[PDB]
Length: 115
Image (cartoon, helix red, strand yellow):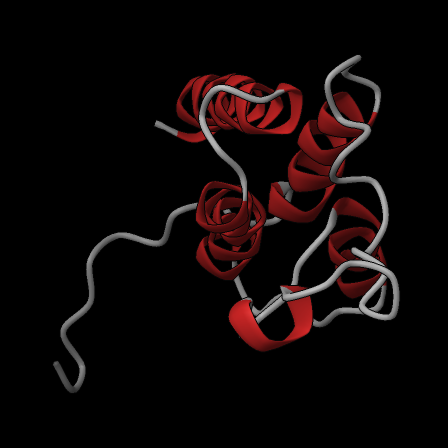
């Protein structure tokens, strides 16, 4: 509350560390469904169904331009990429499997870097 604070966590490396995680996600072999924004002209139903599209290139641009106020807002966009994927793709499809794999990969790196 006012004039009552928990000890200050060192957040000075968060930006660099999220960048590193994001590089690791970008270079994973199962990243291909997520690298670029879904083409809303060419994929029927996507525009109407997925209210907030998200992809790795859009996260990279937000990250590089100071549009994440803290590491939680960064994690929320990464998870949105996988939540979108589950909304639109059967579990038993190449893309549906890619999303589960990437979500796992991310959640481990997240825990190991920050928890």
